[PDB]
Image 1 (spheres, rainbow, N blue to C red):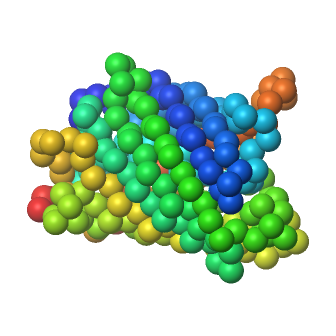
Image 2: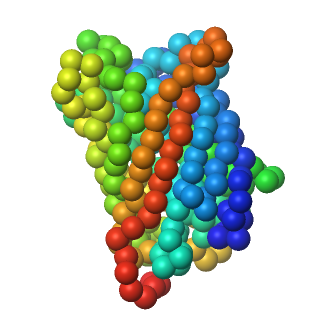
Length: 229
Protein backbone atom coordinates (compact mmCIF):
# COMPACT_ATOMS: atom_id res chain seq x y z
CA UNK A 1 0.00 0.00 0.00
CA UNK A 2 3.00 2.36 0.32
CA UNK A 3 3.58 2.10 -3.48
CA UNK A 4 -0.01 3.40 -4.05
CA UNK A 5 0.67 6.90 -2.52
CA UNK A 6 3.83 8.16 -4.28
CA UNK A 7 1.76 10.79 -6.09
CA UNK A 8 -1.51 12.66 -6.10
CA UNK A 9 -4.49 10.41 -5.38
CA UNK A 10 -8.08 11.52 -5.90
CA UNK A 11 -10.54 11.05 -3.02
CA UNK A 12 -14.32 10.78 -2.74
CA UNK A 13 -15.90 11.29 0.74
CA UNK A 14 -19.55 10.14 1.32
CA UNK A 15 -21.14 10.50 4.74
CA UNK A 16 -24.76 9.62 5.66
CA UNK A 17 -25.70 10.84 9.16
CA UNK A 18 -28.39 10.95 11.85
CA UNK A 19 -28.07 13.25 14.87
CA UNK A 20 -30.98 13.44 17.30
CA UNK A 21 -33.09 12.22 14.36
CA UNK A 22 -31.86 14.98 12.03
CA UNK A 23 -31.08 12.88 8.94
CA UNK A 24 -28.39 14.33 6.60
CA UNK A 25 -25.91 13.50 3.86
CA UNK A 26 -22.60 15.10 2.82
CA UNK A 27 -20.43 14.50 -0.21
CA UNK A 28 -16.75 15.45 -0.45
CA UNK A 29 -14.22 15.56 -3.26
CA UNK A 30 -10.51 16.26 -3.53
CA UNK A 31 -6.90 15.19 -3.68
CA UNK A 32 -4.16 13.78 -1.48
CA UNK A 33 -0.39 13.84 -1.98
CA UNK A 34 0.94 11.72 0.90
CA UNK A 35 4.52 12.61 -0.10
CA UNK A 36 3.84 15.93 1.77
CA UNK A 37 0.94 14.73 3.92
CA UNK A 38 -1.23 17.14 1.93
CA UNK A 39 -5.01 17.02 1.73
CA UNK A 40 -7.35 19.42 0.05
CA UNK A 41 -11.03 18.60 -0.03
CA UNK A 42 -14.43 20.19 -0.52
CA UNK A 43 -17.55 19.01 1.24
CA UNK A 44 -21.15 19.87 0.40
CA UNK A 45 -24.32 18.96 2.40
CA UNK A 46 -26.56 17.42 -0.24
CA UNK A 47 -29.78 17.52 2.03
CA UNK A 48 -29.96 21.27 2.76
CA UNK A 49 -28.35 22.77 5.86
CA UNK A 50 -25.96 20.64 7.90
CA UNK A 51 -27.43 20.48 11.45
CA UNK A 52 -24.01 19.92 13.10
CA UNK A 53 -21.34 22.66 12.77
CA UNK A 54 -18.68 21.72 10.19
CA UNK A 55 -15.63 21.59 12.53
CA UNK A 56 -17.25 18.61 14.34
CA UNK A 57 -17.12 16.53 11.19
CA UNK A 58 -13.53 17.23 10.09
CA UNK A 59 -12.05 14.27 11.98
CA UNK A 60 -14.82 12.04 10.62
CA UNK A 61 -14.43 13.17 6.94
CA UNK A 62 -8.23 9.45 5.24
CA UNK A 63 -5.07 9.06 7.33
CA UNK A 64 -3.44 6.98 4.65
CA UNK A 65 -2.39 10.50 3.48
CA UNK A 66 -0.29 11.39 6.55
CA UNK A 67 3.41 12.01 5.75
CA UNK A 68 5.59 9.35 7.29
CA UNK A 69 9.26 10.14 7.21
CA UNK A 70 11.45 7.42 5.61
CA UNK A 71 12.62 6.45 9.09
CA UNK A 72 9.01 5.81 10.18
CA UNK A 73 7.85 4.32 6.81
CA UNK A 74 7.37 0.80 8.31
CA UNK A 75 5.16 2.11 11.13
CA UNK A 76 2.58 3.37 8.65
CA UNK A 77 -0.49 1.26 9.33
CA UNK A 78 -2.91 3.18 7.15
CA UNK A 79 -1.19 2.83 3.79
CA UNK A 80 -0.12 -0.70 4.57
CA UNK A 81 -3.81 -1.79 4.64
CA UNK A 82 -4.42 -0.80 1.01
CA UNK A 83 -5.80 -1.25 -1.58
CA UNK A 84 -8.36 -3.54 0.16
CA UNK A 85 -8.71 -0.88 2.75
CA UNK A 86 -9.48 -0.46 6.40
CA UNK A 87 -12.60 -0.04 8.54
CA UNK A 88 -12.37 2.93 10.93
CA UNK A 89 -14.71 3.16 13.93
CA UNK A 90 -14.94 6.02 16.44
CA UNK A 91 -17.00 7.15 19.43
CA UNK A 92 -16.54 10.92 19.83
CA UNK A 93 -17.62 12.30 23.22
CA UNK A 94 -18.33 16.01 23.43
CA UNK A 95 -17.75 17.29 27.02
CA UNK A 96 -21.06 18.08 28.83
CA UNK A 97 -22.99 17.23 25.61
CA UNK A 98 -23.71 14.28 23.33
CA UNK A 99 -21.64 11.87 21.25
CA UNK A 100 -21.09 10.60 17.71
CA UNK A 101 -20.56 6.92 17.19
CA UNK A 102 -19.20 6.38 13.60
CA UNK A 103 -18.15 3.67 11.21
CA UNK A 104 -16.26 4.21 7.99
CA UNK A 105 -14.75 2.06 5.20
CA UNK A 106 -11.58 3.63 3.80
CA UNK A 107 -10.45 1.71 0.74
CA UNK A 108 -9.47 2.11 -2.89
CA UNK A 109 -12.38 2.03 -5.31
CA UNK A 110 -10.71 2.15 -8.73
CA UNK A 111 -7.85 4.68 -8.59
CA UNK A 112 -9.81 6.80 -6.05
CA UNK A 113 -9.24 6.58 -2.37
CA UNK A 114 -12.76 6.56 -0.92
CA UNK A 115 -14.09 7.10 2.62
CA UNK A 116 -17.70 6.00 3.19
CA UNK A 117 -19.20 6.99 6.50
CA UNK A 118 -22.28 6.18 8.56
CA UNK A 119 -22.79 8.26 11.69
CA UNK A 120 -25.22 8.48 14.62
CA UNK A 121 -25.29 11.15 17.31
CA UNK A 122 -27.37 11.09 20.51
CA UNK A 123 -28.03 12.83 23.84
CA UNK A 124 -27.17 16.20 22.31
CA UNK A 125 -28.60 19.32 23.97
CA UNK A 126 -30.71 21.55 21.65
CA UNK A 127 -29.68 24.67 23.64
CA UNK A 128 -26.24 23.19 22.79
CA UNK A 129 -22.81 24.17 21.56
CA UNK A 130 -23.26 21.67 18.75
CA UNK A 131 -27.02 21.71 17.78
CA UNK A 132 -27.18 25.34 18.94
CA UNK A 133 -24.34 25.93 16.41
CA UNK A 134 -22.02 27.83 18.85
CA UNK A 135 -18.50 26.88 17.54
CA UNK A 136 -16.06 29.05 15.55
CA UNK A 137 -15.31 27.98 11.93
CA UNK A 138 -11.69 26.98 12.35
CA UNK A 139 -9.08 24.22 12.25
CA UNK A 140 -6.41 24.12 15.00
CA UNK A 141 -3.24 22.07 15.29
CA UNK A 142 -3.58 18.64 17.03
CA UNK A 143 -1.61 15.52 17.86
CA UNK A 144 -3.00 12.05 17.16
CA UNK A 145 -1.73 9.26 19.39
CA UNK A 146 -1.53 5.73 17.93
CA UNK A 147 -0.84 2.29 19.38
CA UNK A 148 -0.96 -1.26 17.99
CA UNK A 149 -3.85 -3.65 18.70
CA UNK A 150 -2.48 -7.18 17.77
CA UNK A 151 -5.74 -8.83 18.98
CA UNK A 152 -7.91 -6.98 16.36
CA UNK A 153 -4.89 -6.79 13.97
CA UNK A 154 -4.98 -2.99 13.70
CA UNK A 155 -4.51 0.10 15.85
CA UNK A 156 -6.11 1.89 18.78
CA UNK A 157 -6.15 5.69 18.66
CA UNK A 158 -7.12 8.54 20.97
CA UNK A 159 -6.82 12.38 20.98
CA UNK A 160 -8.80 15.46 22.10
CA UNK A 161 -10.17 18.00 19.55
CA UNK A 162 -10.36 21.53 21.04
CA UNK A 163 -13.19 23.31 19.35
CA UNK A 164 -13.32 27.03 19.96
CA UNK A 165 -16.64 28.12 21.33
CA UNK A 166 -17.99 31.41 19.84
CA UNK A 167 -18.32 32.76 23.41
CA UNK A 168 -14.63 31.94 23.75
CA UNK A 169 -14.14 28.77 25.77
CA UNK A 170 -13.18 25.30 24.53
CA UNK A 171 -15.54 22.49 23.53
CA UNK A 172 -13.59 19.22 23.94
CA UNK A 173 -14.19 16.22 21.67
CA UNK A 174 -12.58 12.98 22.81
CA UNK A 175 -12.01 10.51 19.98
CA UNK A 176 -11.90 6.92 20.83
CA UNK A 177 -10.74 5.33 17.57
CA UNK A 178 -10.20 1.84 16.14
CA UNK A 179 -8.93 0.88 12.73
CA UNK A 180 -8.88 -2.59 11.29
CA UNK A 181 -8.25 -4.26 7.94
CA UNK A 182 -11.00 -5.06 5.63
CA UNK A 183 -7.71 -6.39 4.39
CA UNK A 184 -7.84 -10.10 4.95
CA UNK A 185 -4.00 -9.93 4.40
CA UNK A 186 -1.02 -8.53 6.45
CA UNK A 187 -0.77 -4.90 7.74
CA UNK A 188 2.10 -3.17 9.65
CA UNK A 189 1.43 -2.90 13.38
CA UNK A 190 3.14 0.18 14.73
CA UNK A 191 5.14 0.97 17.78
CA UNK A 192 3.49 3.85 19.59
CA UNK A 193 3.69 7.28 17.90
CA UNK A 194 1.72 10.39 17.06
CA UNK A 195 0.71 12.44 14.07
CA UNK A 196 0.80 16.20 13.98
CA UNK A 197 -1.77 18.23 12.00
CA UNK A 198 -2.19 21.72 10.48
CA UNK A 199 -5.24 22.97 8.74
CA UNK A 200 -7.77 25.43 7.55
CA UNK A 201 -11.46 25.61 7.03
CA UNK A 202 -12.76 28.17 4.50
CA UNK A 203 -15.49 28.72 1.84
CA UNK A 204 -15.77 28.56 -1.95
CA UNK A 205 -17.32 32.04 -2.46
CA UNK A 206 -19.20 30.74 -5.51
CA UNK A 207 -20.70 27.65 -3.88
CA UNK A 208 -24.41 28.26 -3.10
CA UNK A 209 -24.77 25.17 -0.84
CA UNK A 210 -23.79 24.59 2.75
CA UNK A 211 -20.20 23.46 2.47
CA UNK A 212 -16.63 23.42 3.74
CA UNK A 213 -13.16 23.65 2.24
CA UNK A 214 -10.44 21.70 4.05
CA UNK A 215 -6.71 22.08 3.41
CA UNK A 216 -4.65 19.97 5.74
CA UNK A 217 -1.12 18.92 6.64
CA UNK A 218 -0.35 15.80 8.62
CA UNK A 219 3.02 14.46 9.53
CA UNK A 220 3.98 11.36 11.59
CA UNK A 221 6.49 11.57 14.46
CA UNK A 222 7.69 10.17 17.80
CA UNK A 223 9.86 7.26 16.65
CA UNK A 224 13.68 7.08 16.21
CA UNK A 225 14.98 3.43 16.18
CA UNK A 226 14.19 0.05 14.43
CA UNK A 227 10.87 -1.27 13.45
CA UNK A 228 8.03 -3.94 13.50
CA UNK A 229 5.73 -6.05 15.78
